[PDB]
Length: 417
Image 1: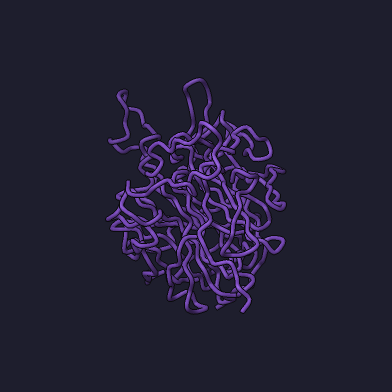
Image 2: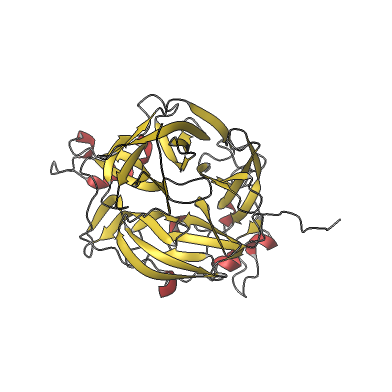
């Protein structure tokens, strides 16, 4: 017997979070310009999911780059959105996007200047009217895709739907996305359920093939199981806080975690829930859109979090947080000491969200709210400038800003059927 250290959740502690520096130029997103272009006058987009293979390679098909987006109609003539003076209030329309979210696709031979493709699934295919985020996985040279996504209301279920991409020299179509399959939902012993917490998270599936074992796993956002308000911020959740920083307040209401599941097969059909990789009890309620970069034989685990969902007595920016391990199952340590990788600038704290770090170091995000004066601001619902980061040991560094929605491919796949 070679005894191995047992698998245990890595704790993101309050002491770790106290290191978060909102004013670090190496971990701040470049300022978004108030004059940003808008992709569509018909729909809002936000969460953006590039087509990729199971190993994480961003993929074009016959030279066409493809992205999937969470999408919502713009409703400029809706009476509900007319203000006191009978003028359209975009903020109300934008805030209602989540309740009417649908999966669209877009394509481009340049990895930018996206051409809208429309709905992935015909209306009525999804068992829930709300389609929330996940991952489009290109399977083979027949152009078959497994779209892993979150079916929301009733409940929140990780699901997948098989279809295929068809290309011509004029553009791209998504066909045959007809049969949504239930994979798993929160169990209540490892991941918190709606019964335990009306505000529970269970979403953002990120399937991947482990580069070391070759087994299929899948990350998702969850909360630590237990009735809302029952969790305890104990010595491990507090961590090594300095004198005067012992008070956890009511931070036991913040219970975010990064979950992982394992597949019994190579087709991603039958999944088993595992205990979480990372827990943030007392630190942050929302460890969103968990995803990996594999580099230098290490596991870089990224998650998107918000200022608003920090534990009592803690703060930090909206943006990218992350951890690094030698091993898939840890132990993980916080990148840059605190976990902060790419924070919004405090002068434009809501400029972007739902970032995605790709294996080439390029980080895509969508524009939310950009200030244009003392009280005035613009709504995006469009792609932000891509920004290159470098991963180096347990450090990250912002390097270079690229064009709006620049998502170049890492591989091209030759498709016919």
